[PDB]
Image (cartoon, rainbow, N blue to C red):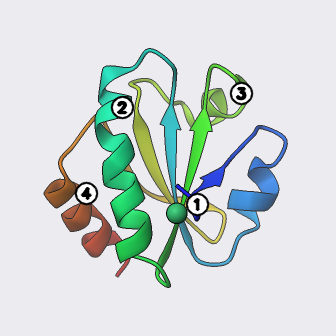
Amino acid sequence: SDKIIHLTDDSFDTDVLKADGAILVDFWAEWCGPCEMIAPILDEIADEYQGKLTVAKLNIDQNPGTAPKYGIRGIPTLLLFKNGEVAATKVGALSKGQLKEFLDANLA
Ligand SMILES: [Cu+2]
C-alpha cells in the first residue's frame, strides 16, 4: 500500500496523464474476486519496481467517469501509461509471474 496512488476522477489527469515515468493503473471495483486476488501482487510489484514504475488504483464504483473514456470492459483491467498515453493493456486476474513478464516486456 503506502507508495501506491489512490486515484479519483478529479485527480486522474494530474496523477496519470501529467506524471513522469511509467504508471501502471489498476481499474478495479467492489465485490470483485479477481480484483482481490491481484491486490497483494500489486503491493509486491510496487516495491520491486520502485524507481522504474509507479502503481496507482482507481475504484470505478466510486469514480464512474474515467473508465468509459478508455473503453474498459472486463474488471480488473491494468493499463500501463507512459507520457500520458496507454502503452499496454492487460485485462483479467493474472499471477505474479505473468505480471512481471508483462511489465518487463513493456517497460523496455
Ligand atoms: Cu507501502
48 w.r.t. 88: above or below:
below
**Which residue was labeled with disc 2?**
36
Q: Which amino acid lies under the numbered mark 1 shown in the image of this protein?
A: Asp
Q: Which mark is residue 63?
A: 3
Does the residue tagged 1 have its C-beta within 8 Å of any atom of ligand 1? yes
Q: Which amino acid lies under the numbered mark 2 shown in the image of this protein?
A: Glu
Disc 3, SS: loop
Q: CA distance from mark 4 to mark 2?
A: 15 Å
**Which residue was labeled with disc 4?**
99
Q: Which amino acid lies under the numbered mark 3 shown in the image of this protein?
A: Asn
What x and y, as percent, mark residue 100? Answer: 24, 65
Q: Measuring 34% from the left and 62% from the top, which residue is drawn there?
A: 44
Q: CA distance from mark 3 to mark 4?
A: 25 Å
Which of the two marks, 4 or 2, is nearer to us in this view? 2
Q: Which amino acid lies under the numbered mark 4 shown in the image of this protein?
A: Leu
Considering only order in the chain, which callout, 2 or 3, is on the residue closer to the N terminus?
A: 2
Q: Nearer the viewer, residue 47 or 18?
A: 47
Considering only order in the chain, which callout, 2 or 4, is on the residue closer to the N terminus?
A: 2
Which of the two marks, 1 or 2, is nearer to us in this view? 1
